[PDB]
Length: 258
Ligand SMILES: NS(=O)(=O)c1nc2ccccc2s1
Ligand SMILES: NS(=O)(=O)c1nc2ccccc2s1
Ligand SMILES: [Zn+2]
Image 1 (cartoon, rainbow, N blue to C red):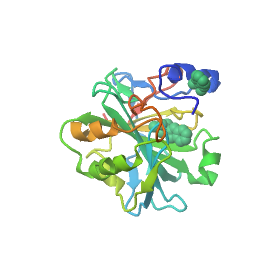
Image 2: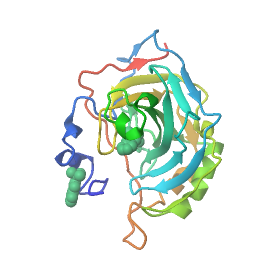
Image 3: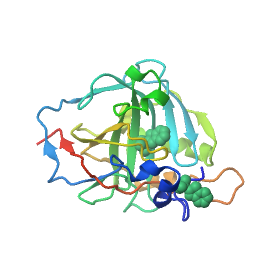
């Protein structure tokens, strides 16, 4: 936790302890919609969350994670650009201090108010720790949030945040259905990238949905009441916990749709 999103330890400093920060396959990136190629060989995504088992929600000092039982194939992502089966381990968000920033990926330089990451690991590697050491180890499904009407399926998340205000706090979070966080369309862009927080490993197939979900101002305002700090420490609101776009370098972004 020496790294963060503060005035002295933010993304521009990370390279000093994680030199891969200046690597060839870093995330997020700007998605230039005119340069992205429609790839008719890409398949529809298969999101199979009917048997998902959420367990717990944790403030880890950089975001909050809703954690799942990933001890068997009960919530998996397949298809799309992927070979094999990827198990859902957690989701979290990145968001801003105001609605005009917060997303990690951008679309023709447009920033959204927030971005949801549903993180999955390739079961061929047996565990998450092994998966992050492989170029096809993870699949992260990214979903933009814009501010408008409330997202009904987000409210259960919103309402527990008071109970995990500070770093290291957790709470039971069973029976949550992550299907309630999806947009209508599963059209997507995809490219090879990285984890966007340390250790920044280049192990991710990114799948970024084109259609944002709408959340209310009141919902995102509650994200912004969380704290980066621990209990009793000087209050530092958990806002602007997003990494900016990184150089695309020698990478092709592909679109699943015309
Ligand atoms: N972002 S980092 O290289 O991990 C980092 N920045 C800082 C600033 C002050 C003290 C420790 C660290 S560690
Ligand atoms: N923000 S993200 O690329 O989805 C992500 N980064 C990290 C870093 C360490 C462990 C898990 C994840 S998931
Ligand atoms: Zn993330």
